[PDB]
Length: 244
Ligand SMILES: CCC[C@H](N)C(=O)O
Image (cartoon, rainbow, N blue to C red; front, top):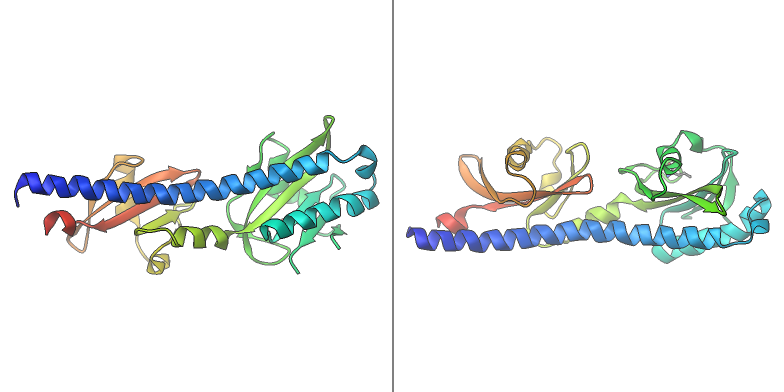
């Protein structure tokens, strides 16, 4: 009851929840940075091959192929590949890299977006054509002496990020670009019929990392969200810690 005591519980739980929100944010950042560094190392190993190893398709197969496979294995990627300007892609896929001419790579955002930036491009989650699993793709236009060799692509199962986020402490969860629930420690939050407007509206009024209160079934809750890349990470708890 005493306003001194209520304030001290509010400050205390505010510190705990925002600490745990940061753990989930860091989880998403570390996932992306690990994958980007992997993709950069692979780009460098392909680009450092002699030109003779790169200028025929058969040489690409025999000299880039093993590299794609060793990298795929090292990180347990789903697919690792190099897309070429003739529309063919050298593909190293889970369950010997082959040159494929039937995957329409020039229509894929991971291909075309890599050509418009000098950075690694990261897709949202989407259904992989090759193995029919949801993936996040990291892609990168590879250049050697200013000449494009092709577009590197690395597919990581989006389930990997979901499991990483789910294992974090706290009632944390993650929205995707379309404000659709993407990951959650509490699996029940993945129910697609749940209305998330209360917590998203509270976030919209308060801003990144700013603790707020909101209502659920006429009961007070506390929470905070923050943008992480194009995701939105949130945490929420009951307000009983301050009220009881
Ligand atoms: C070989 C390209 C594979 C990529 N996951 C896609 O669906 O385009």
